[PDB]
Image (cartoon, coloured by chain):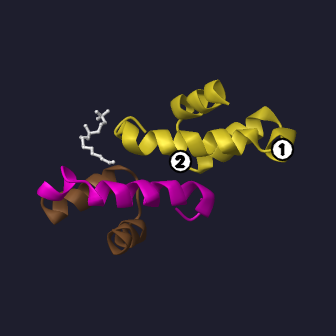
Chain colours: A brown, B yellow
């Protein structure tokens, strides 16, 4: 968010990448994968970046 | 937060541990360190765990 720092967002993005590459996760619909990352507190941009990197 | 999976919260807690171990950070008042982590999106439960592991 607007008052946060990259240091604390970067591990969430990194985990999200590993999440999106995981064989269990990949069996769920794209929207469900995105909703899961949203419930993890990731911003729309962070989710989009995770998908790019995955 | 409570809805987060350990897969995502543990790496964040790990990041908070590194934060709390930092020499400059340790110079700041306790309340300031906790509040900094709160504005990063950690809950008191997660901050307590960070301190526990620090
Ligand atoms: C390496 C990444 C693989 C992650 C693959 C993870 C598979 C999802 C498991 C379902 O998660 P959850 O139960 O919503 O979260 C746990 C949070 N609590 C149980 C609500 C407290």
Look at mark 1 in the image and give the residue it sits on.
B23
Look at mark 2 in the image and give the residue it sits on.
B41
Left or right placement of residue A21 versus residue B23 in this view = left
Both marks 1 and 2 on one chain: yes
Q: Is residue B42 visible?
A: no
Looking at the image, which residue sits at the far bottom? A52
Relative to B40, is B16 above or below?
above
Depth check, front residue: A29 or A22: A22
* Residue drawn at (36%, 66%) of the image: A47
Residue stretch rendered in magenta on the structure: A1-27
Residue B38, image x, y percentages: 60, 43
Q: Is residue A10 magenta?
A: yes
Q: Is residue A21 magenta?
A: yes
Residue B54, image x, y percentages: 68, 31
Relative to A49, is B30 above or below?
above
The part of the image, by quadrant, that contains residue B8 is top left
Asked if the residues shown at circle 1 and circle 2 are in contact, with their CB atoms under 8 angstroms apart, the answer is no
Left or right placement of residue B40 versus residue B10 in this view = right
Residue B27, image x, y percentages: 87, 41
Please give the chain letter of the residue carrying mark 1. Answer: B
């Amino acid at each position: 968010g607007p008052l946060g720092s990259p240091e604390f967002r970067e591990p969430l993005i990194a985990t999200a990448v590993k999440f999106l590459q995981n064989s269990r996760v990949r069996q769920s619909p794209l929207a469900t994968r995105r909703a899961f990352l949203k419930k993890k507190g990731l911003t729309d941009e962070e989710i989009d970046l995770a998908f790019q990197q995955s």
